[PDB]
Structures are given as structure tokens and as C-alpha cells.
Image (cartoon, rainbow, N blue to C red):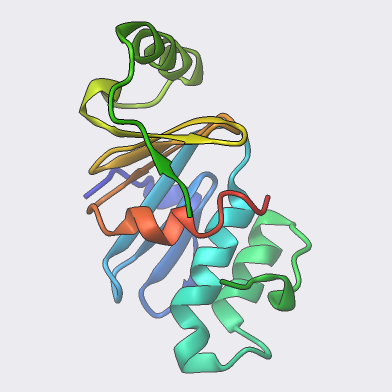
Length: 158
């Protein structure tokens, strides 16, 4: 589980709180924060997808609430539903990816060498058990490994 600052969030469902750079959902046990470039629309899409089953695809209240909180325009209709593992990545690539981590300044240790590395049309994607570094310069940290797929679905869209 990750650190979230009490003062800085907005309640958007019974057990969903949204924060400046993340959200914590205690119903679905999904916690994510991002560092580096803006990933707020990825987080919005994750919220929509989480609550879609309860709301239908019309008015997803928590998604509308989070959009108001972040002052972001994003139509639910835009939120809709795959890539190449590297068998061996050079120490040099690992080392340069580790330097991207330093530039991003995450609140915990990320060791790229523990990640699975993929080549995409935009550069390297590193998928860890508690983090993802994408080639758009965003580092996601999350509370359990299965959150990775929820992120991976939307990181190319925004």
C-alpha cells in the first residue's frame, strides 16, 4: 500500500479518494500515483473502467467527480479497450532507463533491472511488480502487480 496525504484528496465514491497525482480505491483495492509527465487522463480512464459496471456508460459519477477535481475535459465515449518483450537488454539501456528514473524523482526506490522490458514504437516500457515506466516519461507506482494491466490499457491514448 502507498502513502496518500489526507488533506489533499477529494472523495469521489464511497471508498474512492482522488489526490493531486493519484487515487486510492478501498472497494477495489487499487492504488496508483504517477511521477514525471502528466498522467491524469490515464487515471480518469482507470476510474471510469472501475465504476462502469455499477453505473453504465452514461454518467459515471466518480469519473465526473474526478474530472471536476482535476479540471480536465474527457468524454466517457473516448474510453475504450499488444507488444514486444526484450529477451536481453544491455546494461547500457538499463543504465539510461535508471537515469530517466532519477530525472523523474519518485518517492521510492525503483530498480529498472527488476522490470520486464518491452520495445514499443515510442521507446522502452518497463513493467515492474509495483511500477511502470513508460516512454512518455511517466512513472506509475501501484499497490499490487495486477494494477499494471489497468494502466497498460490506457498509456498510449493520452
